[PDB]
Image (tube, helix red, strand yellow):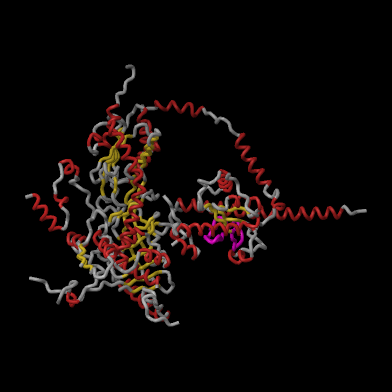
Amino acid sequence: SSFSRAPQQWATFARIWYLLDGKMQPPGKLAAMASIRLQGLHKPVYHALSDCGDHVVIM
Amino acid sequence: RPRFVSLRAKQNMIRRLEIEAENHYWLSMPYMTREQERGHAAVRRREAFEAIKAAATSKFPPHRFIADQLDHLNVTKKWS
Amino acid sequence: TARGTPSRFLASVLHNGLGRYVQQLQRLSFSVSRDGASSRGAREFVEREVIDFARRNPGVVIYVNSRPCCVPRVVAEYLNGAVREESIHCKSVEEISTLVQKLADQSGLDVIRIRKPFHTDNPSIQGQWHPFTNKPTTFRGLRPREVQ
Amino acid sequence: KFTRSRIPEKVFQASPEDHEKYGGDPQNPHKLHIVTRIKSTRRRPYWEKDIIKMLGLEKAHTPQVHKNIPSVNAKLKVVKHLIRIKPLKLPQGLPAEENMSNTCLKSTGELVVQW
Amino acid sequence: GGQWRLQQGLAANPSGYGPLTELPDWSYADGRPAPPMKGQLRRKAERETFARRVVLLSQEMDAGLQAWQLRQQKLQEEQRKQENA
Amino acid sequence: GYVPKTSLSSPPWPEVVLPDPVEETRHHAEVVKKVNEMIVTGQYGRLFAVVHFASRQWKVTSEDLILIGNELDLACGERIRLEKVLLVGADNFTLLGKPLLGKDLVRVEATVIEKTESWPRIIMRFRKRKNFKKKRIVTTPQTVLRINSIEIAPCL
Amino acid sequence: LRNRVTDRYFRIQEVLKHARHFRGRKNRCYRLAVRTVIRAFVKCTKARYLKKKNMRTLWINRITAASQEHGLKYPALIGNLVKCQVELNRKVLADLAIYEPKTFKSLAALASRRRH
Amino acid sequence: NVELALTSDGRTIVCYHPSVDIPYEHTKPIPREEGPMIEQLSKMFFTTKHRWYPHGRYHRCRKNLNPPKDR
């Protein structure tokens, strides 16, 4: 709070980089996590037209 | 194509069956007997049908008023 | 439809309720005909209701022209510069009364689709959510898989 | 052919297990039913539709109070698969004229004279 | 949470009977109560009609039982009174 | 009754122990007193409130505008108290009703700023090949309210 | 031609004005415009159900995201709030998730506590 | 980091949620042609190519140049 308008909007809609470790993991469970993050369904500000997806790096 | 019954469908049917069984129980205990109930509402039923008959037989054209006829002259009311 | 129509956001004129309420209607102009059945209701409204309305709304200047162009009308001018013209053709006294009261009550903002049923200039008190709210910090700010 | 179903009378003879399960005393039975329609009359026979109209259960989930007497019970038996029947309970007795406008039908089936 | 509300004895729908729908939404800043809401007035009228029907049906059934008792008493007393010789 | 530690021996979720009621009441009293002291000393800035008005719940703060989709039988500029407040929150604390907060705690006041009609809404019915076409235009009455102030009192 | 229509211009324009933002000849030719305008109005009428349906879906998605940020699942949050007699609706809960994260954190903690 | 407490009557829940600051130790010191163009832009912004191609005059004229602004 008490941010300026542009920095506040930038912070809210910034895209985060997540890391998944695929070692011994089911590809489907990895995919569920990754798909949620890629869509942005993990953000309370989510909307299909807001382009609020995040980066997912699976190793 | 074949169709199959899910656990949810079975549970829904079971819920409905439980409601119906409770309905059976609550219908199994009449308050009055058929002989006791005979005629106990006859007066009210007769009065209700008397009201229905009165409404049916009171149908008639509405009154017509000279005021209603003459008020139409106001369509040409102006300022002098 | 919404897509074939302009829209706006819910708003007031000059923060109309914060300090005091200012009636946004400032001018009413009734063009009424002496003769002509189209303005009979307007004539009865001028005879019976316009004075009471005027004394109920001292902030509104009411003009009665008694010589209209085309159909009898009421032009409502608001503080924000909006002008809304309503034909009072063939309207009864009570219809005109309700229409005039509606004009008095409403603001000058366009009667178009309003996007949101609410308007806050301070939507957040605890701080708008950003991805780093609720995210724990780490010692020395080490990102994942960072060596040092 | 599809016809009216004659329910055997043993269906409506409660057992002591039923009495314990549902909490109604066969002696001193409840006076009034609260019947609510919980199932559509569409795809049901015209006689069930007619009974629903007679009982005034056209709106679903709208409680209707009826007498617990054999004729009403026969109609309710005809449409028992479309309705929920619960006894009307009167913890404070039937409302007096003074508080006739201050009653409330609790979801438990109790008409309370305070609301 | 309709089942839980029913277990606690409330309306399954919180929009049903309860403080959140039966209390006045607003009042004048002075403190004067607001005029009753249209939905609340309609609901009160419906509840009054339901209560009046409950009273009417209960009284009718009670009067029917009393009339049946009196008919039984009259029949037995008349059949006894016939023994007069 | 002892079961050796296997994957399925215990439920996957961590076991939960109910805190002792004495310490629970002590902690509850401490927290309530702390928040009440914050209210007494005015250690809060903006307040927001979730208020049940009309049929809906509005997240509200001072100077906010609210569009009710019906006429309220109130003159424009008239001040009103919204009596069904479900939640009031500040930067550092919130108060939750069960389901409603008391009249003594919160006072949310609004003002009727506008009484308008909605923009014309089209209701069209159409069924193909049945000559079935109907059109209706409806305008809904509306009232704009401005939330003037939210006040809280140390009545916890 | 005793009686001839003289308003056909305005009758046509009443439909064409609603058709002006269409693609192709549907925005110009009345025969094509009127069919697409009727479809547009029917869609507009039927979309008032889908607006309400989608808003609740959006609220539930946002609440699910916000509650997963605190380890709760949406059913747990909603059910335990009901059991604690907090009657906040999904619109308000999504608004709190976005704009009052600390209040939503409190609600999530309360729901988890009630669960435990 | 929230303190929950029913009041004594049990009719209102009080939540105490102070804002926690980031510890100093959890921080780091401040450090001191069309085809190829669209490929470069797509790689830069992690998008697809389709976003960067132009649009026709019809679409461009359909775009609203004076959109309503809230807050």
**Farthest residue, direction bottom:** F2
Q: Quadrant of the N terminus of chain H?
A: bottom left
- Residue at 28% from the left image edge and 72% from the top image edge: H18
Residue F120 seen in the figure: yes
Q: Is residue D103 magenta?
A: yes
Picture layout, residue H69 above or below residue F60:
above
Q: In the image, residue F32 lies at what x, y percent? A: 36, 74
Q: Is residue F64 left or right of residue F24?
A: left
- Residue at 49% from the left image edge and 29% from the top image edge: B68
- Residue at 35% from the left image edge and 61% from the top image edge: F50
Residue A43 seen in the figure: no
Span highlighted in magenta in the image: D87-115
Q: In the image, residue C3 lies at what x, y percent? A: 27, 44
Picture layout, residue E84 above or below residue C145:
above
Q: In the image, residue C68 lies at what x, y percent? A: 29, 30
Q: In the image, residue C114 lies at what x, y percent? A: 29, 48
**How many labels were placed on the picture?**
0
